[PDB]
Image (spheres, rainbow, N blue to C red):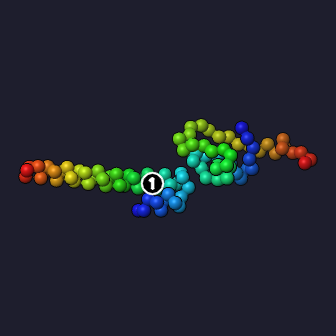
Amino acid sequence: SFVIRGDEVRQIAPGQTGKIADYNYKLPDDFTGCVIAWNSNNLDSKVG
Amino acid sequence: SVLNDILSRLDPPEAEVQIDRLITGRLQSLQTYVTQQLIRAAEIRASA
């Protein structure tokens, strides 16, 4: 579980290319699973 | 047709798709070749 920008969601895929895909969370070309995403924006609201 | 040209160019997922096609083609071609060799081998063997 982690948080990314909404546009970024395309990255979380097997053997995918992208910054997060290369630098932070990479799924294997073999992978089996499902990915779910939603805007925690209300939650992610701080003054800062 | 140049395998490296695929590998150099494409993201891994697409590369595998293109490569799989190329392999399928070459494999089919190699199998056709081997089949040709085998059938010819029969003709040659009959001759032998």
- Indicate left or right for A42 with B2 as reference: right
Q: Where is residue A43 drawn, in percent x and y? A: 84, 41
Measured as percent of width and height from the top left, residue A3 is found at: 75, 43
Residue A27, image quadrant: top right
The chain holding disc 1 is B
Label 1: how many residues lie within 10 Å, few (<14), some (14-19) or many (20+)? some
In-image side of B9 versus A23 (left or right): left
Q: Residue at x 16, y 51 (%)?
A: B41
The local secondary structure at tag 1 comes to helix
Q: Which residue is outermost to the right?
A: A47
Front position in the image: B38 or A8: B38
Quick one: A26 or B14, which is closer to the camera? A26
Q: Is residue A3 left or right of residue B12?
A: right
Depth order, front residue of A31/A36: A31
Against B41, residue A43 (above or below) is above
Q: Amino acid at mark 1?
A: Ile
Q: Is residue A17 in view from this perspective?
A: yes
Task: Please tell me whether residue B11 is drawn above or below residue A36 in the rendered image.
Answer: below
- Which residue: 64% across, 50% down? A22
Q: How many marks?
A: 1
Residue A4: image x %, image y %?
74, 47
Residue B46 in the image: state x and y as whole percent.
Answer: 8, 49
Asked if residue B29 lies left or right of residue A41, the reply is left
> Measuring 63% from the left and 45% from the top, which residue is drawn there?
A26
Q: Which residue is mark 1?
A: B19
Q: Which quadrant of the rendered structure holds the N terminus of chain B?
A: bottom left
